Amino acid sequence: RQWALEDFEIGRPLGKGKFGNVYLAREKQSKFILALKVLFKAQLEKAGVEHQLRREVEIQSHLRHPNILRLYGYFHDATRVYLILEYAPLGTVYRELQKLSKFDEQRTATYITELANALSYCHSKRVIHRDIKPENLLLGSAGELKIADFGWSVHAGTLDYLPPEMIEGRMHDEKVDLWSLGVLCYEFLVGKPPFEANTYQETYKRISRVEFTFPDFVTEGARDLISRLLKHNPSQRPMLREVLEHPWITANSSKPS
Image (cartoon, rainbow, N blue to C red; front, side):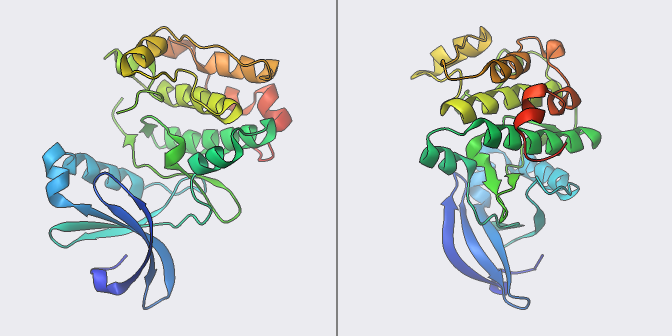
C-alpha cells in the first residue's frame, strides 16, 4: 500500500472498466510490480455504488488464498480512488477462451477445482460470491486461476451468469456459487454460456426454466456434474466438497482438492 499516486510509475493500460481504468504499475521505492485501478468518485456516486465498493474492499481485504486475487491496499485523491492489486501476468480466462475457442476436459476440471477450492475457503469465512464471469477470472504466472472481481457478500447487465433465484427476486444463499460453477464448467467445455441468447428477455426465460442442451462432444461425466450444478432449486445443488470429489473432476483435474 501507498498514500499517493506519485509512489507509482504508471505503465501500460491493462484494461478499461466502466467506472475507471486499470494500469500496470510499479511501486518506485521497492520496484514492486502491481495493478493500479483508478475510479472516479463522481461516477461511483452516480450509481451510488460507493458504499458497495467500500464493503467489497473491506471483505476482499480479509481474504488470503492463492486462487483469489489480492488487494494490497487503497487510497483516494480526491476525486480519484485508487486500488492496489495483485498483477496477474497471464490475463483473463475470457481472452483465453476467445483464443482457444473451448477448453479440453483436463483444463476445465482443473479450473473448476481451483474455483471450488477458493469458494470453499470463502464459505469457511462465511463469504458468498455474486455471479462469476470469465472476464473476472485472471491467470497467475504459473497459469493459476484467480478470482478478481470483488463481488462478495457476507449476509445470507448481462444475465448469463446469474442463478434463477437472483433473477426471480427470490432469497439466495451460498448455493449461488455452485450454480456459477455449472455455468462456467459448461462454457469452458462449449465456448459459450448455456443460457446465451440474443435477447435479455430470452436469456431470462431460459435461466428461469433452466433450459439448456449439450453439444454431442460433451461427455457423460461433464453432463452429470453440470446437471447437478444447474439445479433450479438451490437446495438440490451439491456442496463444494461433493464437487471436488466428483468422479469427472478427480479423473481430469491436475490440481488436488
